[PDB]
Image (cartoon, coloured by chain):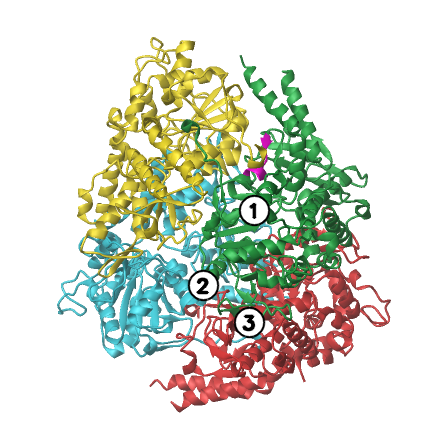
Chain colours: A cyan, B red, C yellow, D green
Amino acid sequence: TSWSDRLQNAADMPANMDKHALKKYRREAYHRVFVNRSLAMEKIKCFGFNMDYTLAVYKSPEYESLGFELTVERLVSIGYPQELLSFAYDSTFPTRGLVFDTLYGNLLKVDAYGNLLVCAHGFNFIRGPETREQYPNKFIQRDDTERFYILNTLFNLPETYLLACLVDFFTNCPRYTSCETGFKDGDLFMSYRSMFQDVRDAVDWVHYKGSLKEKTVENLEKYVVKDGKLPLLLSRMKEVGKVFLATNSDYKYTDKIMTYLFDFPHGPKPGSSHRPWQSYFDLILVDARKPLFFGEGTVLRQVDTKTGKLKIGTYTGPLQHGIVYSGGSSDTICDLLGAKGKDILYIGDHIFGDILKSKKRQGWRTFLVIPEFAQELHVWTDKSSLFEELQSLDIFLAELYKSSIQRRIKKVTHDMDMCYGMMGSLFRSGSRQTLFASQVMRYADLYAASFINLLYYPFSYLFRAAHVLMPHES
Amino acid sequence: TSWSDRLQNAADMPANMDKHALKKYRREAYHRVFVNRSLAMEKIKCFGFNMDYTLAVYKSPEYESLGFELTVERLVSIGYPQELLSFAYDSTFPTRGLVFDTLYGNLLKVDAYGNLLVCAHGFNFIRGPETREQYPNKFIQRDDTERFYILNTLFNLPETYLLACLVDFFTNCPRYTSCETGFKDGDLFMSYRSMFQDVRDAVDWVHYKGSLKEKTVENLEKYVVKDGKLPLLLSRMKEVGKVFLATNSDYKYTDKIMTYLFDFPHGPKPGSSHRPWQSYFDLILVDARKPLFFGEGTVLRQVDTKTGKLKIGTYTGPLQHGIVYSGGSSDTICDLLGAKGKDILYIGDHIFGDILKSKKRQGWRTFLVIPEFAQELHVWTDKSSLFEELQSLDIFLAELYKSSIQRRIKKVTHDMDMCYGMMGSLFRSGSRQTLFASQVMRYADLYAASFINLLYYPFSYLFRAAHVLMPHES
Amino acid sequence: TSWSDRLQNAADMPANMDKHALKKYRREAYHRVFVNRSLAMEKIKCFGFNMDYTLAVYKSPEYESLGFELTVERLVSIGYPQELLSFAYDSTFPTRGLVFDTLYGNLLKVDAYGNLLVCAHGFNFIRGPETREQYPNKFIQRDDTERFYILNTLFNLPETYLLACLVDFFTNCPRYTSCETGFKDGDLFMSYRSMFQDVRDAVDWVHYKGSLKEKTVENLEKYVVKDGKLPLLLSRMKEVGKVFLATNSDYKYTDKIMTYLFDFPHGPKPGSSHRPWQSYFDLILVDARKPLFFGEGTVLRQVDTKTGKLKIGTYTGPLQHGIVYSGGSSDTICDLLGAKGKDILYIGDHIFGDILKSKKRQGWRTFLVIPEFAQELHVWTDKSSLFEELQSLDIFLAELYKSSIQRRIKKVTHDMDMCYGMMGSLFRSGSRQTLFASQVMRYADLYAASFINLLYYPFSYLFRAAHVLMPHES
Amino acid sequence: TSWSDRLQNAADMPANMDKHALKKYRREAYHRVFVNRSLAMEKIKCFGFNMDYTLAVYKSPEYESLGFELTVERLVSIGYPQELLSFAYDSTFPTRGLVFDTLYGNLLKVDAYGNLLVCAHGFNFIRGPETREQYPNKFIQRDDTERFYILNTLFNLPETYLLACLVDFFTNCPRYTSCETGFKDGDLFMSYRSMFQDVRDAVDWVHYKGSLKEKTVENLEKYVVKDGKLPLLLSRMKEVGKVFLATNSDYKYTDKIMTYLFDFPHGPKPGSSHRPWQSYFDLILVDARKPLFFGEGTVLRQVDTKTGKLKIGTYTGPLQHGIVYSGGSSDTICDLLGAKGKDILYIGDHIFGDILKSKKRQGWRTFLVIPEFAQELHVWTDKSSLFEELQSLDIFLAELYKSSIQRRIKKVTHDMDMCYGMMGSLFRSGSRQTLFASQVMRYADLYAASFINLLYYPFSYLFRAAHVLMPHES
């Protein structure tokens, strides 16, 4: 049972729009919308979406394996050794949000301050004392974007496992000698940095040049979660305001995906005429080039929706029914929709290019979609006694200042983490929070395992957060 | 009664080193050390300081007025109009941490997300509806460092008032016409940006070229808080670890200031031989060039302590008794003191160049000195019933979703803010926190009105913070 | 009769290696090597080549038309209008070395100081008075590389004609309105800059992604000049020193092209065993990435000559027989060949990425191959009486300072230029020299219509230039 | 007899404005204007000047020594050793235009291609074979502006000698050890780069902060050449067009200098009322910030000619009688004077910031003032038999290809060079031209030892250059 299974199970249930069942449905955790900063729903005039992993949620682990397999074949096709074809994607290993260190070839899990929580070389997990030889402060400067790459996305999931697979292979293949910053193969030296780049490159290639999008569109039921509730919600959003799409993907892909997502013998409610996905949107924009989209942007173009190709030149006309946009900026959306930032709830999955940047750069309200969260919640409520026991040992160890406690703490931590996978929870490693966690609280006003949980709150709802107080203020 | 008075009153009391009186002294707020992230004092091996507004706390408002007067004379000396000499520094107006907008010439108080809390043009406070003509989202991109300058420091206090003084003068002088981005004087157009730069420049000039440092050193009792408790604390720090200084200031100034700060007929305790300020330090470093200091740094030089001038060339020798350093980097301190980041508690007052950067870039533990805080605390504990009434009206207005409340909220907010000054608290405007507040919590592990509050905790103390939990985790 | 015909006619003649016939052959202009700076051939220890338009000279106009046709189809394939398919490459229009002005959409011919010689909008040649509305000083800042693109190469020939074709089409198509900086198509505005970029992009695409290289290799006799004299010369070069190749092209293409160029039933002389093209080289280097090659370079890789693919990682071994290199730098060639700059005569065709940069950045001796020059010479010696008449009218107009002369000067100039084409000589427009001319003199020590003219000088030859004197020095 | 003596001797003679004596005066070399590119004087509508070393020519070696002495005292004042005070400026050593190599601490004389002509370490002249250990190709990349500083100006003359003085001192002082890239002083290491920077800095300091300008203005007869012919020429320039000034210097200095230069009991001709220097100018501009002046420039300000200080803000009014400008750009001059580039003859002395940049960036016509040239000419016409003998030995050595010649060539070269000084001619080292020479020909249309030689040509004069031909074109 993966996280995408949990979502598709909730996707298969019709929507019960009784005002009481709604209140009762969103009492269970898996249908709640969690609040990091207070949000008056009546002040939202525009609802924004990205597509990939928001409207279209890719079924795990089928889609990650397909991304892995395609990437492995691309590397082999440029001269990586054949053994890579013996690799197989293992969803139990990678947790989203790790930091790969191109200098020493380590996958690292870190907190909001760049403190090392977990270090693994290949599939070898390094313990506290042994990491200090390369990380003498148990600390990394995340700002050093030349050395450290953060695997923020679910697209990064297959490369996350791959980078481990690769380090482990070369470490243990006798044709290579291991060195501190890479592998020596007689007279070729492959640094972890160039090995990293090759992977990064081959992932890019399978999305933009290879067959990933092709093989996806030929089996959408296998790879894409469908939910008849999705047209319902969007329809209701259009009743109280405006709805727009701003995806990085291209209109041909966006047309294929969006058509499938709306492929039902009915419209928003069962029994209504079916409507084309574009009619649920007031403004459609593709090739968004996020995060550059929230700054200067790119040139605003117009799609020829028959040919799928862009019209030549810069588009200077107004927002029309039917028109589809390419490029532009976040200001394009504000100007054409007559909106201000805090009028806009922008629903997305990218913690950086969607959520952080629209908040910092524009003042947009944010809703963060976390696919895995559907499985993350399950593990949490089942294992809450372990975390409660952990909270207990911390408090007791704090009283002790008036030694076997510290070793029991590291043990219940280890056991709790493993329930989430080899790399542990998305949001923490024991009692210590992650960089990812920290970002979700700081930048995502609302968050959930799917934005469909918004169907279950009335449109007048005041999401409430607790006010933050400084130490001296309590 | 200013904040510097509160400190100098606590500075004049001898230290009562009984283990009970200590516990009892640090129960009152004004002597507590507040904790944002847990800190084991036994893990600190090195204590770091800056000087200005940390070891040497400049008496308010005497020092701000001297900085103001000198700056006003410098502007007049390059052809600003004479009326500036009629200005007089008013400590009730400026609050540290404001953002000056060089485009529209407004002083702005903003929160962690760049939300406008207070906007003032000159001395004219703009209300909510009227700000939206220049700030259509009530929002500024703080990242636009070409348009927005944040007045982080107490050195920025006199220019903060000056920029208002200036806008107000030109607005109301009939020789000028007001325009949106500056003032037109017949055929000269002075933009708020160039007016800003001139000020910024004249502040720099009085510190580095003018007579500010001179006039300070000729009346140190008037301008610098002295506390016989300061040698005590440093001595105790040297008993359990190493102590270092890293100031941006120059050795001649640092020698004058530091000598005064240690000018007592005794050493650390009354009755002990007096020691020279340098002997309380394991490593002294001047011309630190923070924040560049925590990155690549500058070249490490050696001071000729007799002449006050630097020796020629790059210093390549080891840490010696007596030697004084110039430039270098934070790695210089680690290497010479044999320390790792989390071994170091670095005590400073600059929220950016001291605290934020040593944490993000190095993994240093941080203690933030907030001078004004001594007065900020006083206003808070006296007016806690106003804030409690505010907290009450927010909760009640939240229940109301089952209109005169919203106008009473803005009224008790206004009254509370004014008690702090015309620009309100350092840390908030009503129930909404500031950018500054947000940074103190995020980057300063410990904070206080003076680092001398550390004298009152034993050296084994485990400062404790509450663990942070995500919404779904409670 | 094009220039490539003149070369292929000389290529078809066997080499007569009698010491007298050599001296007599290189007396005619078409077989001379012209000298801009003195060059002792005995001091050359290494001979360097690029490939495209040096070893492999592409037959005109067949190859330019194929590049044009392919480029036109690529633009149509991204939504340019169909009429482009009615275009046909016209070799009489473009002269290499023009400057396209992306602001006003003009092809421009300019001198060493950026003085306008010829301005054409589409196919409309603007006369002196009319250009001053956009060029008020008859001058362009060639340094403004954002506005001006110099069409240096023979690869740029088809886009040179295309950019004219395009401007002329849109100017005169009624579906568009002409404006100063581009064309308005209802609500799309196509600037000359974006139209330029699209072309630049589609040229890049046909070389690197399209079928140009494919269609070339399937008809090498149609598209590539072959000369049995080429192995002879290279063999003799290897007898007195070392010979190397450094091409931007890829090893698969370089293998196909180079094999054809050496495809003869004999080796260097008729009757000798045939040798494989690689054996004529001491060091082979592909993917050179010139001009970046003469600075920091790229990473040195090693080609797997069986698969055509690069080996993975950085190559750290020595120069071996058989090895082929990828990337690297000019220092790679010096180090492996044990050479200094002035030991190296580097033979190439790119006035910038080959010749200028190897001279300025490294101190290499340079030989510039100018394909067109074979036709340029023919026009010059036939029309020398026109140029002599021009020289005469200038001198006479200079004496006149003690008006129909100035109009006769512009008339004989016009007539002379046209003999070279619609855009005139590569090297001049009348008595005024071009930017290109100026660069050849300043940066190319030797130059010729083909480097094969070097076969006709003994290996001890001291090429001689006249010493340059300053005015006051004569 | 220095070069400034030759000028001041010509400055002391009244102007004989008979049309015959003029023709006869400019037949001698020392009063000719030499032509690098043809120039119709009737097409000049605006005459431009800088001031320092053009209108005001500083008397040698008095002014260089004063610059040296002041600079030496400034270095001593920041802790350089006392022995520097034993240095004394020696005008026989430095030639303008050398390249100092901050890596190996060598003064170098180089040609247009960065070929080493002369290398001196301190005062030790390195011969051909010995330079190849640091310069293996006898070649430097002049583009590497981090390593190489070109001493273009006469202001650079005293530092040129100083850098030698310094290297020689430290090399031979026993308190220091010499190393490849600097000097080790126990535990301080002074690199030639930092030693260079210190000098560069101390030269800047004496001009802008020290007493150089002060001590100049208190003895203008000692330090500044005065010529009553200067008002004459400018007056005649104003009769046929417009005259402007654009100096980097400040208005207070420019007022002091310019007043002295016009201090005569008469105006342009003897017997005319004296006029104030400003009235000879249509547009005066100070703080020009060349070469940035010929690009984007700085903000246009207006000087308060009574106070010497700038008015506050940006000046937006028109060109008025009496107004003085500060900053701006070259476009400011064109717009206010209604001129195009080729309308403007700009007379200056800086080969880069004046001449090269106004030509490349704007299309200005250029006149280059070369102070030293008055002495350079004298040495040349006296020693023409040595150069003729040199030209002879080169030709003979070229015939010899059908060994004591090559050693006689290096000997007559050495003897010829020394007549110019220890570093030889400005324009050559033997038969090989310098980088400086090359630039004068390429960028200065006209040049002379003083622009006063323009008085001797009528205003209709067509300066003539020989047309340049490519090898194949003769």
Q: Measured along the vertical axis of the image, is residue C318 above or below residue C457?
A: below
Occupied quadrant, residue C186:
bottom left
In the rendered image, which residue does mark 2 sit on? Answer: A439
Q: Observer-nearest residue: B19 or C222?
A: C222
Q: Amino acid at mark 3?
A: Met
Q: Observer-nearest residue: B43 or C433?
A: C433
In the rendered image, which residue does mark 1 sit on? Answer: D19
Task: Verify CB contact (< 8 Å) between mark 1 and mark 2.
Answer: no
CA distance separating discs 3 and 2: 38 Å
* The stretch drawn in magenta includes residue D413: no
In this image, C14 relative to A401: left or right?
A: left
Q: Residue at x 25, y 38 (%)?
A: C68
Magenta part of the chain: D432-438
Name the spot of residue D168 as percent of width and height, x first: 75, 38
Q: Nearer the viewer, mark 3 or mark 2?
A: 3
Name the spot of residue B368 as percent of width and height, x first: 62, 68
Per the image, label 1 sits on a secondary structure element best described as: helix
In the rendered image, which residue does mark 3 sit on? Answer: B195
Q: Can you see residue D416? A: yes
Chain to which the residue tagged by mark 2 belongs: A
In this image, C81 relative to C336: left or right?
A: left
Chain to which the residue tagged by mark 1 belongs: D
Q: Amino acid at mark 2?
A: Gln
